[PDB]
Image (tube, rainbow over all chains, first blue to last red; front, side):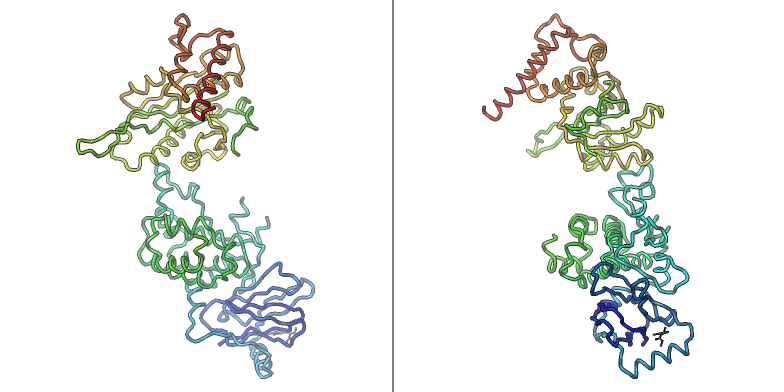
Length: 300
Length: 237
Ligand SMILES: CC[C@@H](Oc1ccc(Cl)c(Cl)c1)C(=O)NC
């Protein structure tokens, strides 16, 4: 079990850790989060009490280093840092643990939610989407735009999601225009899976990471990316059977976790209705269709 | 963006553009079978691709053999239309290729866009105008070449005949759409109007009769009367 200590909490803030969140008051004696499950990526995120604008946060994996959060009064935000002195880090974590100034990662034993949301998400792939190679953790916020969005302005602060575009030469083989546009299997299986992602695990990891950035930060380009990756599978007539079954599980947990009040902005009516009722895969997403119909029948 | 009443004179500027109408690409007769079921029989069709500034009409004849063994023909017809328009553009010298293609039905946008991915700088546009190009098969010489074709064929026409020698392209297009609107609303009446006077003939190299300027004013007035009446006859007014 791992620990992300905090220098202090000088400003009132709502702190998220994965799907959990708690309120910290201005200058409350808060010194971090303990008992964080090893083996998964995690995200620690922030919304200031004075500015519900800019949700922001850090993707990290405690196996890759000892990390802590400190508020920067110049840049006005909680920053993740790495302490490379392991002695000093255990020594500081034990002090705050003894004084019981840490919240415990509040996982219920039966509860596989976070695993199910991050099953294919790898820190090394996150760090290629979010390019800042001097750090081992990755910053994301509500406003960051995607490479594809930048094409349609600061490239250093972009989300380098894999560009998907259904009306592009990459997607459409000369002489197979109608075929490749109505049945995207070539684009999914040869261009993206074999060519770019290499395997379905890396594809699902990017899909899950895009969903989570859309949910935790309201990141609009991430939402676009998540729906595009769903639509590409659903609009392919030929998809490995293992991928369809896993996609159904992935989406089920995503829909389950989505805040009920955010369904209006985070769910694209067209994509979902196409995917569940018109696409080749309309009969292949039984769990996802059932939770969608029982939880968001309005969208459909 | 979409072409409408407000950006209408853009049709007659010096940027090369084409209207594409697909309404006569896939044409059928519906009939009863011996068992009393219904079946369709395809007849020859055509793509109607028109330069509204010059009157040049690229009539790509669609022979019924192109549908043999194919499914979902109405969907295929849109893609076939886009394939043929893209081949037309590629066949033209660069300086004759259009800057814009305006489709008369929105369902043509994605097929044409996908077929024209090689031409990122050609704008594919819809229109809010309700253009009467479906009535192109009411022009006898166009119907004739479509129905006689035994194989795929492109035939080139000037749909304005020699009118541009005397009128502007705005006026020529207005006359064309009035004639076609009239033929669409009441083909028999419209065709009676055009031919009632046997002394005014159609030149071998033309589609419409050789009216004088004054006779065109009378004809045009008769077409407007026809259209207004049918509008009454139809809505009772
Ligand atoms: C700049 C003082 C601050 O420095 C830190 C260095 C490393 C860690 Cl892991 C933390 Cl949580 C803090 C501190 O309060 N050290 C006890």
